[PDB]
Length: 54
RNA sequence: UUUUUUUUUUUUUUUUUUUUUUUUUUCUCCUCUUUUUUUUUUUU
Image (cartoon, rainbow, N blue to C red; front, side, top):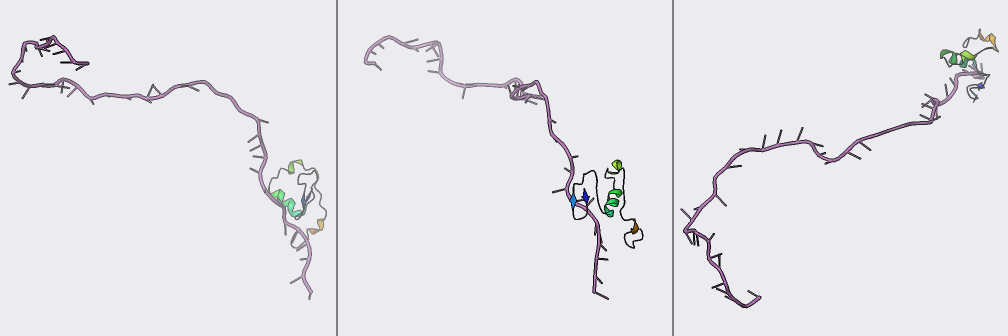
């Protein structure tokens, strides 16, 4: 599944690939997806130093 | 000489029922005068 802002495909797939703001969007609410999460992996950790998105 | 990112129109449907017009009041109440009562009869 792809949860990018301008393309939404198969939002119920086993594996979801999304931008970072989507993760906090589904973490503010319950969304009943956290119960079945085994691995969550980050691809670019060097944005902790980002001046506007860190 | 001005880049990068910020999801979207609630889920559900394959439940049983053996009655019958109406419907419920109003009180006792001084009748004036020629009479017995005439009468057959025939022409429809």
